[PDB]
Image: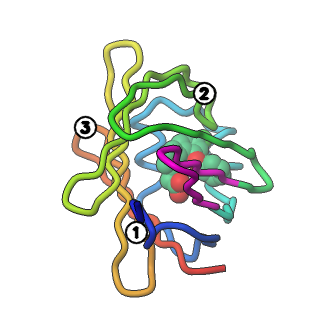
Amino acid sequence: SHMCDAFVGTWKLVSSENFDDYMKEVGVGFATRKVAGMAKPNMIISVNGDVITIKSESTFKNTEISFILGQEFDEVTADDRKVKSTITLDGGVLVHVQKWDGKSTTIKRKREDDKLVVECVMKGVTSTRVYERA
Ligand SMILES: O=C(O)Cc1cccc(-c2ccc(Cl)cc2Oc2ccccc2)c1
């Protein structure tokens, strides 16, 4: 159905801003922030039918989620939070909401020019992570 076509592919992190602050807001501890903040993950997005898969490979952690839009799932984040996640498409933006311990964070993923821009928001803190095709 060509849902998410423009996201599919292999992407490499090329810039980050305010990610340490976003991680602090989320509750990540010092040593994990330092190691995760160094990483330059490879994000691999694919679609098979209604199922979207987002994999991240890095020297820190490798992660993988598979999901159907609008349908809540279990996720273990790279910092080992056990969260309940729902991912939707809103106006061509992938919106990923994570709920845990009465907290919430939202991760938005959008295509902008030849980049895939990832915006991570926790309370008033935003981190912007820019990916290019690998
Ligand atoms: O995907 C994005 O770029 C933004 C992004 C989105 C959602 C979660 C995290 C994230 C939150 C905490 C920690 Cl410790 C690592 C994290 O990701 C990683 C995973 C591997 C390597 C580095 C950061 C990063």
> Hey, which residue is sitting farthest bottom in the picture?
113
Q: Foreground: 117 or 65?
A: 65
Report helix, strand or loop for mark 3.
loop
Residue indicated by mark 1: 117
- At a point 53% along the width and 22% down the height, the residue shown is 74
The relative height of residue 52 versus residue 7 in the rendered view (above or below) is above
Q: Is residue 94 left or right of residue 19?
A: left
Q: Position of residue 48 (x, y in %)?
A: 58, 52
Q: Residues within 10 Å of mark 2 (few under 14, many from 20)?
A: some
Instruction: State yes or no: discs 2 and 1 in contact (Cβ < 8 Å).
Output: no
Which residue is tagged 2? Answer: 76
Mark 3 residue crowding within 10 angstroms, few (<14) / some (14–19) / many (20+): few
Which amino acid lies under the numbered mark 1 shown in the image of this protein?
Val
Question: Residue extending furthest right?
Answer: 59
Instruction: Give the alpha-carbon distance from disc 2 to disc 1, as whole Å.
Output: 22 Å
Q: Position of residue 68 (x, y in %)?
A: 44, 38
Choose mark 1 or mark 3, whichever is in front.
Answer: 1
Which element type, helix, strand or loop, lies under badge 1? strand
Which of pointers 2 and 3 indicates the residue nearer the eye?
Answer: 2
